[PDB]
Length: 431
Ligand SMILES: Cc1cc2nc3c(=O)[nH]c(=O)nc-3n(C[C@H](O)[C@H](O)[C@H](O)COP(=O)(O)OP(=O)(O)OC[C@H]3O[C@@H](n4cnc5c(N)ncnc54)[C@H](O)[C@@H]3O)c2cc1C
Image (cartoon, rainbow, N blue to C red; front, side, top):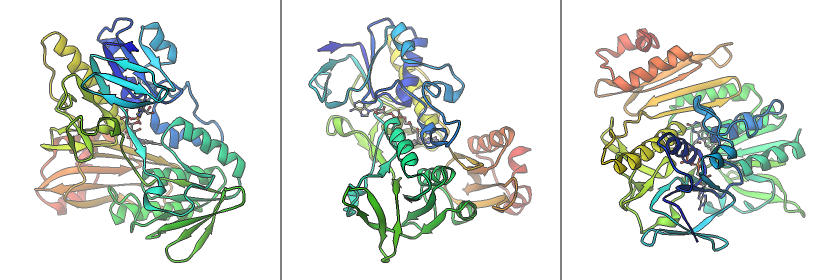
């Protein structure tokens, strides 16, 4: 049995950023441990569906370790060991007892703590949840962690020049379809929803991506459902069957149908809210000395006066800093300001790149040029509720223009006339 004053459970983005805050706050050797089921030090996860999948000049570790993704310094495994921070890799915790402050691994090793920081992220929803026949076939892959990314890279080489089907229509389904196309695959996207990224995109925003992807050679089958998979004598996938009877040939199948907060170890031990571990404005759970950050946390989103849960890389870096600041502040009888996060998400595929700030609530106003054949497309959208701008999206914006739409989402400016807003468009944020 090993004991540490602070234990971080998980080794992803929030864990790496929490360790950086711990080092900045002064942490003595032997105080902090990080237990991860992955075999590598914390890395910037968004790179896994972007640069990691490039056919040439691909991003590889140690290059994209935290905190380079936000302009910070790189944390190789040596960064942890030189500071006396024990990085405990390839160790999966299968039991957590908050009353006895004990975590147990699959091989039976036990770890105790004084402060626990839950940073377990999300697990992928598999097609087994829907009872999809043949979902267990080989070459049917998911993409969450670097292990999956290495498997995907290897399968891309083995089946290069063949047919790929991506199941899912969110930003992951779009990013993986783009990745398979640039790796010389014949790619089809199947998703039951009427348009891609239906949780954020409107039909107007999605129409641009659908037409852009079609020009790139991708077949976007919206309003389509994969009901089964054919496999050969070897067990490898050979086809994806759809609800309508149509069959698509497939050498590889990549799935991106979402995830769920990885809160299993603590069910019944902590208060929950909307699928996440409920926390206050400092990320502390219903259990004193237990904190929850990143994807797992359902926290007060101060500017919206509601409890919210997000799958954002900015939130994962920021909530980690906030939780450590609160823990270290408490040691000196000090308090820290309440977490004031502005929702921010971004995606990348082909030569495109969009940014989203705020809340996608109310009615939307599309501005700019949404022609997918244009050499430099630049369009966006504003979300208006109660006569104020709540959300802002922009594809093809510059650093100045992205800061302008982030400024608009933060200040929630009044829209006196939507006729004037439709006249100014992006200039409304830029002025
Ligand atoms: C492929 C991909 C692309 C993305 N692209 C974007 C993007 O463009 N923009 C954006 O804003 N966000 C993006 N995201 C989301 C963003 O990366 C996440 O929100 C962020 O990584 C979550 O931080 P986290 O610390 O909460 O979780 P994670 O980064 O997932 O870390 C959780 C860690 O806990 C570990 N763990 C879990 N359970 C256990 C256990 N029992 N024992 C030990 N270790 C355990 C996991 O192995 C992992 O290391 C992307 C995510 C993925 C998967």
